[PDB]
Length: 377
Image 1 (cartoon, rainbow, N blue to C red):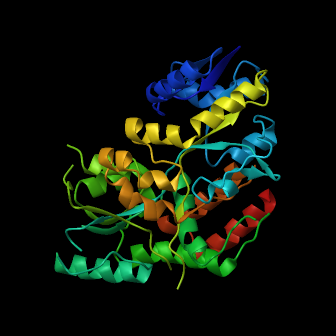
Image 2: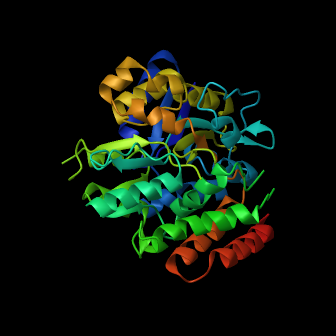
């Protein structure tokens, strides 16, 4: 007999998770689940977990958490581990994303990744989707000379700029955190690459001002040939928008390197202060099961955490473009898994934005980034 309280904020479709929870209660007699959205305002919801975990409040059982937080929350004492848990059935970088001190400390809820959205219509010039940044530059040169921004990416000092820095870093096969493993040449080459788009006229002069939804709105307005963005953008582009039926979805370019993207989306954890550990873990196992991932794809348009569901006929009938998402999500890489992710993110995004704004050079940016990451790690 358990009453389980689960934290799902108002921006994560708690209304659709509620339908999955109703199916769980109908076959799990004696378990009631109640959704806590975190308070009446957006700010209250964003401060909810810090409030009840700092108080060691034992009433919360299950929590949705960002894929960047597993290590921070486990190290803070906020989350329980799932002893002996196998994450091999999920998309491949979930095991790495959720293993902290050799323990599984969260389970996947729904996936996300960056995609290279592109104007399929303009590629008119006989160009196949670019597989390298040099191909993307050549492609942008051909389309722009023929006809409009070549490439929109996030240069504001936000989490998206960390993801931006890491795409060329990962493409060279480098991992920034394994403990800090800083490759100066790869870090300088990443910063120079993003700045080269501005210098070569492929990206606008003020890309340092571009947040995730600025890319989305500008591509949607027909002003962008190539756009880096996440899964939520597609429905905007195909909605009531000036790019209906002119949007392709591809893997992000490589630098002789590898085509990579970022592992995004959200996960579930169990509160370390829950008095109902076993029942809370069983609920998380259900919410992270393939049949629930499938339900959430069909009913909330959330990208599944199992590769097989991108080929499932019921999913692709409901959301055809998920077939085109699969080859991109299979290239995902995990952002640094560290309890000091906040400081690692702040240092990287500050450096990326400062180089793109023209406030510092790539070389001094790598210098500043290595110095600050060494203090944190």
